[PDB]
Image (cartoon, rainbow over all chains, first blue to last red; front, side):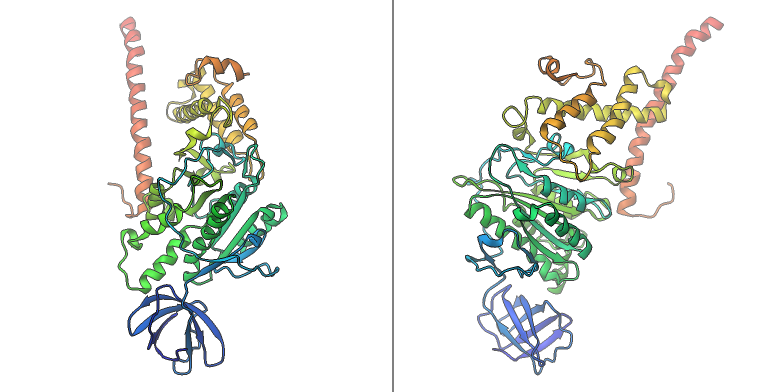
Length: 452
Length: 47
């Protein structure tokens, strides 16, 4: 045990007369009044080691304090009894339930998946949302994020997807791993109250990191969830759905750590290694050859100033297959969920939708309703520039389509689970307004099969 | 140029206004080319 405290600068402190210290090693401060505070190693030198205290350095006397080095980083006490239990950002219990005897202790970092060992995601996931399951299909093993903004209803949508996520005819229940990263106590309570009231907590393992908790606590929170999701899926063979929000607060926690080490930022005031940092977490997913389990990651981040060129969504788009984008204009009109499908894309939707997958008309109706909206939206604008007199009989139907597609298709409700069957049939009803001559993408073999 | 404060948020807003402006310029000239067509047949008849 060491009682050698040399420097203390804010929540950071340095301990001299050290040996064999490692990076990100857990420490324990023994104060002059007997109070115990924990810490992590942010930097090690041969004769000294800097550590950030979680609880802070408020009231710590350097001369009469002591520090204990544990010799191990942040590990997760993993076990199968974690189902139904809610922890914090450091794996500590939060629901005050029974203790969990760890089956193993795994470091939260994880391992890099061999790209040739990775398997192709082939199974469709019914999220219950028409705007997602039909036009931006999620696949079992895909990295598909949700680009939101400050004030956009991303909390209601996060509680809806994890509640309505199910796989067809598999006869095995989906596993949900939810990880709240630096959210408020109100938004955290909204998530916890929704998982308990619907019985989804019986399928979920929740990690809850608040906003006032330390920055080093926010960085480990995604590493805690993915290590357990890695264990549930790859060690046990479960199908795991990983949900994380807000992802932006994880990046700000890296900045407080990066500035604590006096590292010069990169683009837009963020650390240079962010691309490695985000890809390390986003690529711990997908089905593995030889294993029945799978990990599905759905990050949720709010874009600063609603900018897509910001480093947080710019690098995420380079790592994840597609993106789900929410717009502030759709939310202020009453469209729930306000998911704009024009800038949203799914890089694996082709395998997810088809015969055996969902229905034969999934790919055709997607491409038909996609072009019908862009033409209907430009027609409504033509009525604003050239007046309604310039709109023909066909343009009046296209303008009526977009208006209904905004209010009846995408606007379904944060508590409305629509099956894949009810979703496709609604698209045909909205497409039944336009004459057949308008519907060109759909072949007449299937157009004469479902069109009312 | 119109007076504005330089910001990343203003850049994207002026980017969207120009795209709608450029298309609106296309549509009003189409109305200009169109009016020139129904005017010309009527004008020659009136003359």
